[PDB]
Length: 139
Length: 132
Ligand code: NA
Image 1 (tube, each protein chain N blue to C red):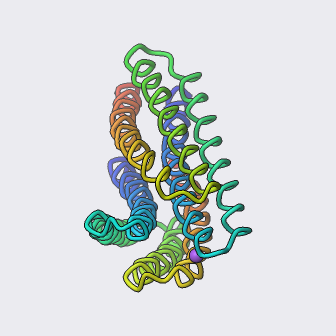
Image 2 (image 1 turned 90 degrees about the vertical axis):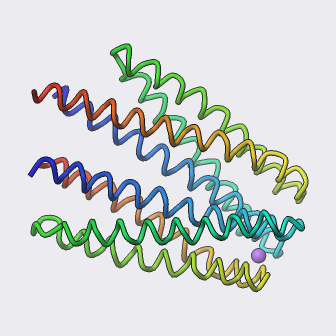
């Protein structure tokens, strides 16, 4: 069952990253829809972008809540802090979309991409660490 | 065997993360073209293409290795929904090359709906994989 917990942790992480990138795919494609005049579809993509990032944040919190050992807990709290940066950048992108402003969009698009780069690396390190811990249990 | 399940998990997870990043990149590049960052846009498009190529290869590997009767049908579904997704993102890149906002809108729901199904299917495949 500690074996079971490692898998549940890996799954939180994998879903969190996937939904976080989906959230960015929705704000940028939503912005394009908006500029094409499809305001209702853009508004649903904004809401979807909100909901995806909020679900990722919640899984990251669960991931911290379940990280006991010192190796894991420190990487996990840095993922949590990095995600906050990412979430704030995407919220910035959603408001540029509501305000129809390319200028504000480009201003935070780069912030989002740099936090997202750190999130991917943190995920890889956590995946390796969790898989190491599961394998040491088996040994 | 247990070694093969870790390789299959890595393939599936990397495939889906690169696949969604491929769409986020072509949408970003489109927005860059709208604001005149044509050089910047071309870098996103190249990345979108490469990510699509790499994730397609990982999906294909995942499927070739998923011979078990328990996985066979789910792995084939993954491959077909992934095809539907990659064709939608290729449509986004073509709408970008054509600088067509309307064309882009029309393929957006194709890509987003398929990715929503890929996320679900991913969960079931790793459940089935974690069943050893
Ligand atoms: Na549009």
